[PDB]
Amino acid sequence: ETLVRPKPLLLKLLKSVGAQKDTYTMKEVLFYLGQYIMTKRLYDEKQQHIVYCSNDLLGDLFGVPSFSVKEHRKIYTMIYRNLVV
Amino acid sequence: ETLVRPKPLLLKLLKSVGAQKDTYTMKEVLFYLGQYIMTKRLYDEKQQHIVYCSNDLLGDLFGVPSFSVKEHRKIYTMIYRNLVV
Amino acid sequence: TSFAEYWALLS
Amino acid sequence: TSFAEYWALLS
Ligand SMILES: [Cl-]
Ligand SMILES: [Cl-]
């Protein structure tokens, strides 16, 4: 599959949880970005699709205070903006 | 699919990351147990299949200092021991 | 549903 | 490979 190139904030984010390359499959981008959200426990305790981005590297990348995981297009759109595909 | 009943240590472990039931599909047991490992960052930074269990609730449940994720049977065997299927 | 599941559902 | 991927490979 094609390799995508994370922009700096998202590269910093992926590396912060042990990714070690400049280019990645989308599938790996999604693995490490999930790992990161859980590693920092930014998910809501009771409604676990809600992610809190305020005052985190993620909110700097995404440009929102919070989002819902269920909004698939919205999440891909935010991710692609942080990638050179 | 069948619902399994976590034994107390593993129930404590699943609840510690927001699972809210006494019975669960295996698939959900595996989702929350993965979430937990990442939430506590017990995975090795450089070789990410290695999980450190020393001095954690997980090592009390599993009965090991460390394990490799790649040892599929071994991981299921440890999990079933912590479940009434 | 865990965050992990919801996440996995993106694919 | 991330821990997340290795984990997902259990299923
Ligand atoms: Cl990597
Ligand atoms: Cl639950």
Image (cartoon, coloured by chain):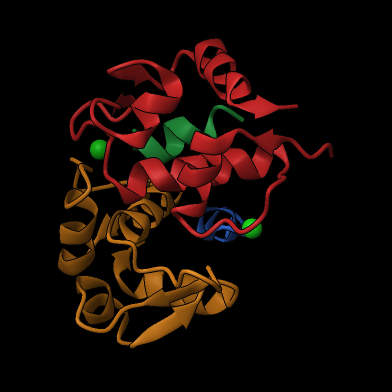
Chain colours: A red, B orange, C green, D blue
In the depicted view, which residue is nearer to us: D3 or B21? D3
Q: Residue A51's quadrant in the figure?
A: top left
Q: Residue at x 31, y 65 (%)?
A: B83
- Quadrant assignment for the C terminus of chain C: top right
Q: In this view, does D8 lie above or below A42?
A: below
Q: Residue at x 54, y 70 (%)?
A: B49
Q: Is residue B62 above or below residue C8?
A: below
Whole-percent x, y for residue A65 in the image: 27, 18
Q: As drawn, is A4 to the left or to the right of B24?
A: right
Q: As drawn, is B13 to the left or to the right of A23?
A: left
Q: As drawn, is A3 to the left or to the right of B42?
A: right
Q: Is residue B2 visible?
A: no
Q: In this view, does A67 lie above or below C1?
A: above
Ligand 2 visible in quadrant: top left
Whole-percent x, y for residue B74 in the image: 51, 80
Q: Residue D11's quadrant in the figure?
A: bottom right
In the depicted view, which residue is nearer to us: A38 or A77? A77
Q: Which residue is drawn at 23% across and 64% down?
A: B10
Q: Residue furthest right?
A: A1
Q: Residue B62's quadrant in the figure?
A: bottom left
Q: Which residue is drawn at 67% across and 54% down?
A: A21
Q: Can residue A36 be seen in this view?
A: yes
